[PDB]
């Protein structure tokens, strides 16, 4: 089993800690933790290509997309590797994150270690927003907080 | 060619940006950038095992040492993978860094992507200090700033 971690920070009050664990090579990855300081409701959640925080979250590049596919969310084969849909902040602006994803990995050519996890201002429309950008990015607005994904003990 | 980058931050004023470039698999890695806020003089400069910033630089773990060697200088055969050259700050607190290292790598068994770069309170003694601890850590004092090493464009 392999593990990773990410501390999310930005220019505002959004802060979080997200853990990753992958029991088997090419197996599902458990993603869990908490993000606070968010507005209630849906916030886009993505792995961006570059683990480059030199210009804050702006230098993280586009969605991690090694298979050169369209943006999506629900369907494993019809998304970018980095598309992790939305986190949901409850009434108190805390998102309790707990999901399992079978497309990201902590090794091999879908590996996310050394890349940037980003939480967004707005909901990701999952590719169904009805415009061209929806199929590129999901229209999730600004990057509120991010961090580089590191190897964990 | 591949590339990496690291933004070093801590609780004090020490901060910086360090770039990595490796033109060939298992070839030398150029390491260059700048760190500010430092006391004039030598400062230890290490790759630590874990890219875990959840307890600040403390959660980075030990020197990256996949070959289970003693601590040394970068030019020694007996060294940890993570034992890089000390950086040197001028009077104004700025260490402009430019080195090459042939033991770290951006892929393979010595890969440092997803690990942590740390700049220290004082000089690394290169394992030539006059105590036992010298050949464990190099006696470089506290961890002033650190960051996770990410994939760059
Ligand atoms: Cu160190
Ligand atoms: Zn995004
Ligand atoms: Zn996407
Ligand atoms: Zn060492």
Image: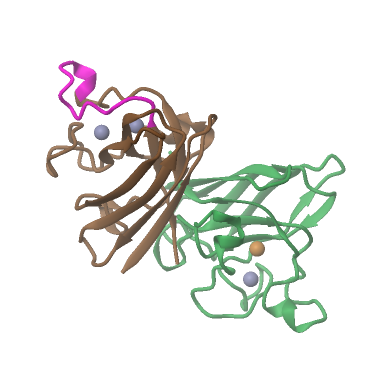
Chain colours: A brown, B green
Does residue B90 appear in the picture of this structure? yes
The answer to whether B39 is drawn above or below residue A68 in the figure is below
Outermost residue to the bottom: B132
Residue at image coords 54%, 66%: B103
Magenta span contains residue A129: yes
Residue at image coords 28%, 58%: A108
Residue A144 percent location from the top left of the image: 45, 30
Residue A28 percent location from the top left of the image: 21, 58
* Count of all numbered marks drawn on residues in the image: 0
Outermost residue to the right: B91
| Quadrant in which the C terminus of chain A is drawn | bottom left
The answer to whether B144 is drawn above or below residue B153 in the figure is below
Q: Nearer the viewer, residue A33 or A53?
A: A33
* Magenta segment, prevailing SS (helix, strand or loop): loop
Residue A107 percent location from the top left of the image: 30, 59
Instruction: Tell me: B112 left or right of A100.
Output: right
The answer to whether B50 is drawn above or below residue A84 in the figure is below
- Per the rendered image, the range of residues in magenta is A120-134
Magenta span contains residue A25: no
Task: Write down the quadrant of residue A91 in the picture.
Answer: top left
Ligand 2 occupies quarter: top left
Q: Nearer the viewer, residue B124 or A47?
A: A47
């Amino acid at each position: 089993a392999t593990k990773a971690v990410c501390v999310l920070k930005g220019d505002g009050p959004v802060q979080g800690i997200i853990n990753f664990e992958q029991k088997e090579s090419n197996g599902p990855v458990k993603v869990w933790g908490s993000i606070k300081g968010l507005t209630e409701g849906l916030h886009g959640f993505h792995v961006h290509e570059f683990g480059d925080n030199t210009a804050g979250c702006t230098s993280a590049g586009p969605h991690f997309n090694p298979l050169s596919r369209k943006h999506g969310g629900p369907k494993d084969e019809e998304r970018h590797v980095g598309d992790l849909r939305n986190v949901t902040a409850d009434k108190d602006g805390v998102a309790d994150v707990s999901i399992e994803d079978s497309v990201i990995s902590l090794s091999g050519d879908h590996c996310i270690i050394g890349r940037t996890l980003v939480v967004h201002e707005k909901a990701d429309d999952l590719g169904k927003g009805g415009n061209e950008e929806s199929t590129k990015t999901g229209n999730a607005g600004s990057r509120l907080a991010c961090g580089v994904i590191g190897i964990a003990q």
